[PDB]
Image (tube, rainbow, N blue to C red):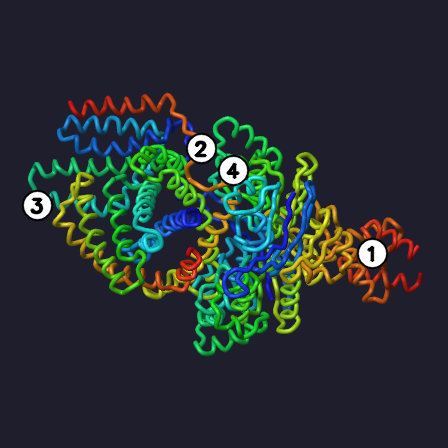
Amino acid sequence: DTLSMVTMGVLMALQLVISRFSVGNNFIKVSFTFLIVALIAKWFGPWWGMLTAAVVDVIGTLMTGGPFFIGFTVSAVLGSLIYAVFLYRQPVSWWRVIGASVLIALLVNTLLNTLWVTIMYQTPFWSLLPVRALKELIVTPVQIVLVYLLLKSQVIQMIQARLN
Amino acid sequence: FGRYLPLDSVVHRLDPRAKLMLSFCYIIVVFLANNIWSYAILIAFTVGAILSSKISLGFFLKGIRPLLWLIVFTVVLQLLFSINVTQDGLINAGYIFVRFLLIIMMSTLLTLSTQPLDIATGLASLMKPLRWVKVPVDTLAMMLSIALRFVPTLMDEATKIMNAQRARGVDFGEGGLFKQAKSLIPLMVPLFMSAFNRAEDLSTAMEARGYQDSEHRSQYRILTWQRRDTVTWLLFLLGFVAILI
Amino acid sequence: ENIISVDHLTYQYDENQAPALTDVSFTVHAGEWLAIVGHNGSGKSTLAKSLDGLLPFTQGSVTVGGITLTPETVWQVREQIGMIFQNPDNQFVGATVEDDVAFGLENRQISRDEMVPRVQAALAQVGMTSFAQREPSSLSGGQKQRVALAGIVAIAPKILILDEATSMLDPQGRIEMLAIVRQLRQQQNLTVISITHDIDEAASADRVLVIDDGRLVDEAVPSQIFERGTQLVEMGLDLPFTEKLKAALRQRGITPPTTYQTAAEMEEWLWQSLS
Amino acid sequence: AIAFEHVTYTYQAGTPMAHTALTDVSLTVPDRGYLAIIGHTGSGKSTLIQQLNALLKPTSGTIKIDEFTITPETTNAALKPLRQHVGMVFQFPENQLFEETVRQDIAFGPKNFGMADADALALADEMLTTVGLDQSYAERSPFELSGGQMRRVAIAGVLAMQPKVLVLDEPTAGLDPQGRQEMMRLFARLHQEQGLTIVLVTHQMEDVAQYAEQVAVMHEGRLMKFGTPADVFSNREWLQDHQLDVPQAAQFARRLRDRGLTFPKQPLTADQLADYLAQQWAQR
C-alpha cells in the first residue's frame, strides 16, 4: 500500500525505542514491546504481523548486542500470530485479549525456554521452567490490562479511523 | 541507535553480509564441537577475530553483564546435581562457562563492529532470495529503512515530550509502580500521535516524489564484496574443517 | 503550464474536515512565479495538494502539460511537478542525504552510474555537497528543505510547488531557501507556484491569487496587493515596512501616498516632503 | 525577580565527551520584566531557559528566582514548586496534549501540584477563555482541533498553573501573520495585567523591539551585552557579526539619515519612527 506500509515502519521504529526501556526495580523489569506487536497484529496481521515481527526481533537483537538464534525470531513470529488471530478484524474483548496473552505467555515461557536450554546454553530445562513460569505469570495480568487499555484508548481509535 | 558501532580504522571491519552469515554460522560450530582439542580451535579463531578487531577492554565484559542471570545459575546448578560435585562436573563448567563467553563475545563483536545502517543494507541481501517463496523483501527493506531513520527522531521527540510534561507536574520514576506506569500515558499517548502524524506526512511526500511499488526500482545503496569477504571466510572454514577433525 | 477549471472540494461530513475549495479557476503560464495567499483555513493548502494526485476531487479539472489530472495518469502529472512541503522534519526517507536525493531517481528505475554524478550535481545546486553524508536529524531544517529541493532538481521537473515551506524556518532558513529558488529560475527556467504567508516570497512573485472563504477572491501584481494595508494580515500576509510606516503616519495625522512605494521610493517621498 | 550569578553549564559531568553550553552567565531581570533572549541556534538560549525551572541545574554558579535558590547541589525533590512558579511553554507546545477532553488536559498541571479535581476543572474553564476559546471547545478531544487551536489549548494548560514567570520558547513558530500577532498581543495583555514576568526566546527582531524591556544577546554559550533594546540594537555591524540584525525600522531610518534627517533616539519601531517624522512634519 504505502500509508499502511509507512505507518508499520514507524511502529517498528517505535518498537525499538520502547525496547531500550523498562519499568521495575532491581533486575526484574519488563519491556512494553508487546504493545506494538499487538497493535500491528490488530491493524495489519497476521501476514504482515509475522513478517514485521521477524524483522524487528532480528534487527533488534543484532543492534543491542545479543546472540542471534533463529528460534527467537520464530518465537517472535508466533506472538504476532497469536495476537492477530485473536485480535485481527475482531472487536476488542476482555477474553479476546486475555486468551491471546495467555496463549502467548505459555509460549513466551515454554517455547522461549527450550530455545536457550537448547544448545545456546546448557541451562537445565525443568529447573528454569519454574523461574520463567514464575516471572512471566505476574507480568501477564499487566500485559492483559495494558493491551486492553491501549487498543480501546481514544488515540488508537482516532488513528484506526484515519487508516480506514 | 545505541552508541555502538565505534569507528576503528585499523581493524579489518568490512563486507557486512559476510559477518551476518558469520555471526549466524558461529553458533552451529559450538555444539558441533564435542571433544577437547576441538575447543582449542573455537578459541583460536575467536581470539584471532577479537584481537584483530582492535576492539578493547570491558566492552566484551559489558556484553556479559545482562546474562550473569544464567551464567551463575547454570554453572552453580551444574556443579551441584552431577548435592555432591564430581571431579568431572567442575570440568563441565569449563565447557559451559567457556561456551557462554564464546556466544556472548562473538555476538557482541558483530554489534560493535558494524553500523546498523550497514547491517540493514546487509540483511536485505541475505533475504533477497526469499522472493522465490513470495516474501516481499524490497518493501520489507523499505519498512526497516523507514524504521531506522525514525528511531533517532522518535527518541529526540520522546525526550521533548517528557520535558514538557515534567515542566507541568508529572514525576517520571517516582513514588510507586502503578503511579510510575500511570505517568507513562502523558509520554506515550502523545508519542504515538506524533509518530502516526509523521507517518502520514512522510507517505504523501514519498508519493509526491514518484512512488507506487517497493519493487520496480533501483538501489543507490550498493554493497561491494572485497578481498577480505573471501579470505575472512576461508579462515573461518579452515577452522571449521578442523572441528570435523 | 497548468489550467484549473471550476474546481471544488469537500471531505467527509458535512462541510468541514479539510478546507473546502469552491469553483476555483485560474491559469499559470510556463515560467511564472505564482503566489497563492489566503487567510488561515482557506483552501490554499488544499489547492496545493489538488495539483498533485493527493486529494481526490470529484468536481472540476486540473490539467498539467496537456495531461489532464485524473487517476491512472496522476503519476505522469506528478512527474512534471516537484513539491516541497511545509514542515521539513518530515518528508525525508533516507538515513543519509545522498540516499534521499537519490530516492526520486530510484523510483524512475534509474540505476547505477547515472545517479552518482546526478545527485552530486544536484547537491551542488542547493549548496549541500559538504553535507552529503549526514543523517536528517543532524541538520537545521532550512537545510533539510534544501535537500528536499535537491531531490526534485534531481528528477528535474517543469513546475516546482511550494506548499508553505518557509513557514516553519528560522529567518536564515527562509532567506537562504528563497534565494536559490530564485537562482534556480535564472537557469532552468521553471514554473514556481507557491502557497504562502511570507511577504518576501509573495514580493518576489509575478502574480498573486487571493483565496478568501473557499473561493478565488482577488488576483493581481503584488505591488498592487500590498496596497491592502493593515488589511494584509487578515488576508494572509504580513506587512511590508513602508506599509507599516504609512499606517503609523496616518495614526499621527499625516496622510501618505495610496500606491505601494518601495523603501527607496518612500525615502524620496519623505525627504521631499521634509526637505 | 531572576538573577543569574556566574552560572555555567556543561553537559555530561567531568567525562570528556563533555561540552559546556553556558559559561559564566550573570544577568538580572526585575519584577514584572520582559526578557527577550536572542542569538544563533546553539548559543545556549535553550540551556539558559531550562535553568529557569530546573530541568537543568547549574554546573556552577547560583540561580535565584524569587524565594527559590538553585545551586549545583540543589535537590530535585526540593524543586517541584519551582515548576509551578515558572511556566515553560515549549516550541510547538501542541505535542504534549493527551487527555481525552481539552478541559481535562488543561486541568492536568494544577492536578499535578495537588489541587482538587473539581477545582482544577473550573480553572480550566476560566483558562479556556483567556486563551481565546468558546466553552464549546471544553468537552472536545484535543485531537479534533486546528494546529493553532491546539497551540492555545496547550498554552492555556501552562497558564492554568498560575505561574509568576512565563517562559516562552518561540511561541509563534509556524503560525500565520495574524496568528502570530494575536498570540503576541495575548502575552502582552497577560504581562500588563496579571504582573507576570516573561522570558521570550526569539529569532524575531520585530518582536523584540515592540514588547521587550530587556534583551540578552547569546553568542556561543556566552552572553555578551545586556541592555534595553536600544542598548543592544545600538551597533548594527556589531550585531551583524554575531549573526543578528537590527529591527526593520532601524534600517529604514538609516536611509533617512543619509538624506539629512536626524533623530533623537534610534527608531526601532515604525511607531517610534512615525513619532519623530510627525514631529519634524510639524515644523517643515
Say which of D284 and B203 sits in front: B203
Say which of D260 and B75 sits in front: D260
Q: Indicate which disc, 2 or 3, sits on the residue closer to the N terminus.
A: 3
Residue position marked by numbered label 2 in the rendering: B219
Chain letter of the residue beneath label 2 in the structure image: B
Secondary structure state at the residue bearing disc 1: loop
Secondary structure state at the residue bearing disc 2: loop
Chain letter of the residue beneath label 3 in the structure image: B
**In this rendering, the label closer to the viewer, 3 or 4:** 4
Residue position marked by numbered label 3 in the rendering: B81
Name the residue type under label 3.
Phe
Chain letter of the residue beneath label 4 in the structure image: C
Q: Position of residue D75 (x, y in %)?
A: 44, 62
Q: Residues within 10 Å of mark 2 (few under 14, many from 20)?
A: some
Name the residue type under label 2.
Gln
Q: Indicate which disc, 4 or 1, sits on the residue closer to the N terminus.
A: 4
Residue position marked by numbered label 1 in the rendering: C259
Name the residue type under label 4.
Gly
Marks 4 and 1 sit apart, C-alpha to C-alpha, by 45 Å
To which quarter of the image does residue A92 belong?
bottom left
Residue position marked by numbered label 4 in the rendering: C104
Q: How crowded is mark 4: few (under 14 residues within 10 Å), some or many (20 or more)?
A: many
Marks 2 and 4 sit apart, C-alpha to C-alpha, by 11 Å
Considering only vertical position in the picture, is C112 above or below D276?
Answer: above
Looking at the rendered image, the quarter that the C terminus of chain B falls into is: top left
Res. C97 in view: no
Marks 2 and 3 sit apart, C-alpha to C-alpha, by 57 Å
Kindly indicate whether the residues beneath marks 4 and 1 are on one polypeptide chain.
yes
